[PDB]
Image (cartoon, rainbow, N blue to C red; front, side, top):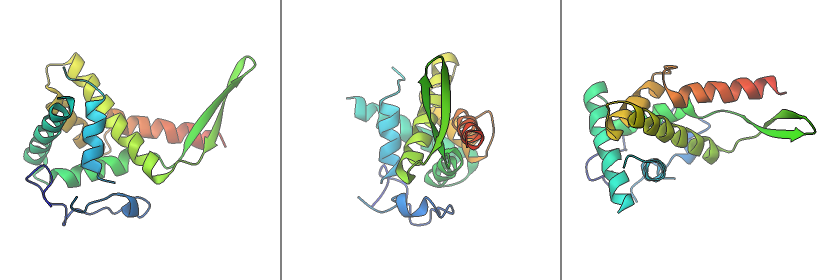
Length: 166
């Protein structure tokens, strides 16, 4: 019922019609659980409790910085970082080719969450920000469609390559 024993999702809105049916905002596709899994597979040196704590602190930071429900900000970040199409490489002979392909709703989410965790993990490793602060910053940047966001910039890149590979 309560996310990480504190937040509610009943007032969180998914305005992107293409993702709304696949983002689970109901009590026990749980995006928070998915994010934790992505963070768990990144870094920031049980592994699950660790990732859980990093995400929870990141949410507290997001709420303080934006003044909004952290889960809602994550949804915006996901919606902004989820590419609407992708491509598959085919390096045959001496040249690699790009081909635009369908990307499923759940893979769109997985890509966005993976890139958010990757961006956070990268900033953390190289700056004086804790993993939680980097994750909060990455999520906020993505939610605001700010190119400084790794996930968002990656999303633009993927769609750019896909639209050109048609």
